[PDB]
Image (cartoon, rainbow over all chains, first blue to last red; front, top):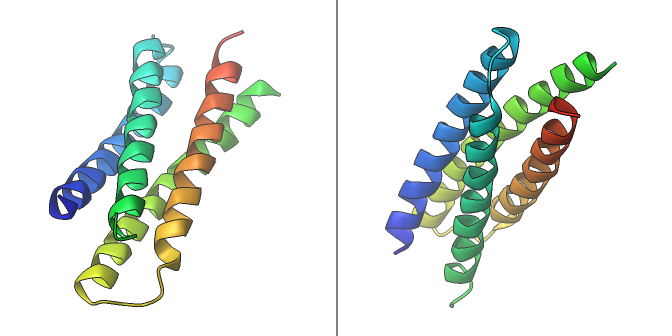
Length: 61
Length: 64
């Protein structure tokens, strides 16, 4: 599922950029970024888990 | 000085995530290609962990 891992990684990482951008603006519109901060939190955890799986796969695992 | 500690955290995050993306892109190429240097994968692992610690700071700083 290396094909899929890479696909998800790229999609999740893009989404994270967007999310960081959205949060930057949310602060400056004086806005509730809380839910978006938390969503970002889980997003990085999910990337970490996918990169960890990528490392297992790359290792004859 | 939390407004500059925030503004720089936002900057680190953006650059670090953009880095992570390029890395995903380069690592893919390396796989299709059988490149023996796997260093971009471990740099990618390092990048998420550094993104994780930055975002955590940004959270702790964003709200008392």
